[PDB]
Every structure is written in C-alpha cells, then in structure tokens.
Image (cartoon, coloured by chain):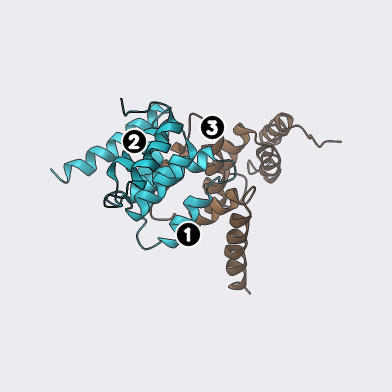
Chain colours: A cyan, B brown
Amino acid sequence: SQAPNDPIEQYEYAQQLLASNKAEASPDTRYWLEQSANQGYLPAQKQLANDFAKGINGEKNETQALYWLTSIALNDPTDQGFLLANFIQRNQDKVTTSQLTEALYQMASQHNPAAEQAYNQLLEQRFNQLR
Amino acid sequence: SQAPNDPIEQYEYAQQLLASNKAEASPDTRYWLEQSANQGYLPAQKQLANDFAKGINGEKNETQALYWLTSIALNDPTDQGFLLANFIQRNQDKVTTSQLTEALYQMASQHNPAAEQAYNQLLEQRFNQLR
C-alpha cells in the first residue's frame, strides 16, 4: 500500500518521489501534491501553484496555476491575494481575464450552485471548440 | 452622538440614511457602509461592492468594486470568488488585469509586508502621472 491518505504524508511522499531524481520531472510528484492540495494542505497548494506556472513536473497550465493561487489567497491569512496579484502583474502578457474568470468559477463552484452553472458553461464552450 | 461604532448598527444607519431619500444618492450611506465593511461585516461589503460598481451613492470606482468583491471572496464561504468572477466576465471590456492587481495588493497589504511594498509602488506610480 504505497498510497498515503493523509495530506501531510501525501505531501511528503511527493517530495520523496521528486528526490528520486529520475528525470527530475516527476509526474507522480504532481499527482500526490494534487491529492494533498485538494484536502486543503497549504504547502501542497503553494508547490502546485509553482508547478503549474513553470511546468516543473509536467505541462504548464496557466489556468490551474491561477486556480491554486486563488486557493492560497482564500486559505493563507498572510497571503490574501499577494501571490495571485504578483503572478498576474509579471505575466500581464500571458494572463487573460478569461483564464482568471475560469479559475475563479472553478473555486467558487464548490459551494455555490450559480458558480457551478457558470463554470460548466465555460467548460462546455471551451470543449465544443475543440470538437 | 449620531455615530455608531458597532458594524451592525453602522450598516443599519447606512440604510436609514438612504431611506431618507433626499436625492437617493446618499454619500453618507457610502461612508457608513465603509465603516461597517472595514470591520468585516459581509452585508456592508456586498452593498459597497454594488455601490462602487454602479455608482449608487457616489462616483463609480472599478478598482474599489474589485477590492470589495475580493474581500467577499475571502470572507463568504459560499462565494469564494463567484461575484468577482461574474463581475470580470460581464465587464471584460472595462476591467483590466491592472485594476485587479491593484485591488489584490490592496487586500494583501494588510498582513504581508511584500504586498504593502508592491501596493505602494503601484499607488506612487499612479500618483506621479497626475503630478
């Protein structure tokens, strides 16, 4: 059972896998950070925000970077938007209000039925263009 | 002493002043909403967000609208970014990532020294252009 369920041991397992330094890109590091971050573990959310922004353990994903930055803003009383603001500021050329809208609805959709409808509408239109 | 110190009575005084319906624009309604909102009273923050967005009790102010929307996201567990996202989405033509950056640093500057420096840098540059 090499499969932690507690967010602290998930986060630590992610570091352990990364330290194995196979290719230094560790997709399972991203996987375990996500499990940890989804249970609200702030260190995992911070690492995941950097991972998605920079493409550390996998592809870059600006919208998911913005999502985790938003999560950090909501859950770190000494952040309250600093990392998100600085990311937008230094990526003014790449970050669109559209990506930010999607990340925000993604966050809001957890406890707000109106947000879940708007989020799904964005996803469905983003998908029917690839279709 | 027509000057409440408790955020609930401030909020209620704001409604009372507004119901006087002098010009239906009530700058003192905005004033008391701000006192209430600054002590963390969510109903005041929501009304103030609408006030700044629409110019109800005074001039419009998109950056302050975004600020209070951010505050609502951080303090309303069933919002978590919905009102902010929807505001950006329906004002894509007016809202700039620059205004959002300023609102976010304004929020973050309360408990983050790095945010306060970045916020002041934005303010100082915004002021030296009018100078």
Between marks 3 and 1, how big is the CA–CA gap?
A: 24 Å
Image quadrant where one finds the N terminus of chain B: top right
Label 3 resides on the chain identified as: B
Circles 3 and 1 in contact, beta carbons < 8 Å: no
Q: Quadrant of residue B44?
A: top right
Residue denoted by label 2? A118
Q: Residue at x 49, y 51 (%)?
A: A83
Q: Position of residue A32 (x, y in %)?
A: 35, 36
Q: Nearer the viewer, residue A127 or B55?
A: A127
How crowded is the residue under tag 2: few (<14 C-alpha within 10 Å), some, or many (20+)?
many
Amino acid type assigned to the residue bearing label 2 in the image: Ala
Q: Quadrant of residue B41?
A: top right
Q: Residue at x 36, y 49 (%)?
A: A51
Task: Say which mark, if any, is on residue B98.
Answer: 1
In the image, farthest residue toward the right: B1
Label 2 resides on the chain identified as: A
> Is B63 displayed left or right of A125 in the figure?
right
Task: Say which mark, if any, is on residue A89.
Answer: none
In primary-sequence order, the first of circles 3 and 1 is 3
Tag 1 and tag 2 share a subunit: no
Circles 1 and 2 in contact, beta carbons < 8 Å: no
Between marks 1 and 2, how big is the CA–CA gap?
A: 24 Å
Q: Residue at x 41, y 47 (%)?
A: A49
Residue denoted by label 3? B76
Q: Mark yes or no: residue B89 visible.
A: no
Q: Residue at x 56, y 46 (%)?
A: A79
Q: Position of residue A10 (x, y in %)?
A: 40, 33
Label 1 resides on the chain identified as: B
Name the element at disc 1.
Answer: helix
Name the element at disc 3.
Answer: loop
